[PDB]
Length: 50
Length: 47
Image 1 (tube, one colour):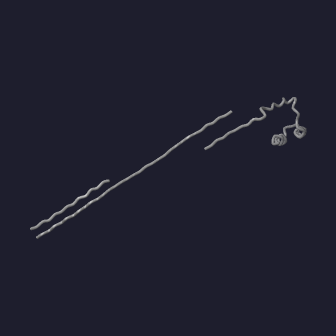
Image 2 (cartoon, rainbow over the protein chains, first blue to last red):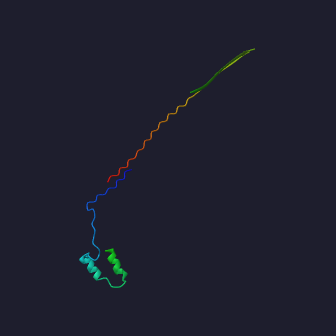
Image 3 (spheres, rainbow over the protein chains, first blue to last red):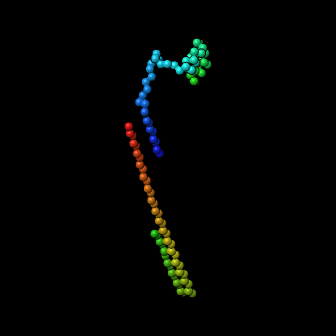
């Protein structure tokens, strides 16, 4: 039996800003703009699927 | 190695009768065994 488990990291980390300074992707923002403003779970489920 | 062997002879005269018998048996057994087992493990951990 062999097990080899190996990692390289080359970007030590990224740290994304907090949500107040993040910019949303235009398609995602456009999906949020069509969310039904009520608990139509089908819609938010499709969003979580995407 | 095991052997058991017997010889018997008789003659009688009075009339004459004789009987002679020889019986022999040999038994041998040999058993040979051999076995080999080897085991090894490596761990290497590097950072």
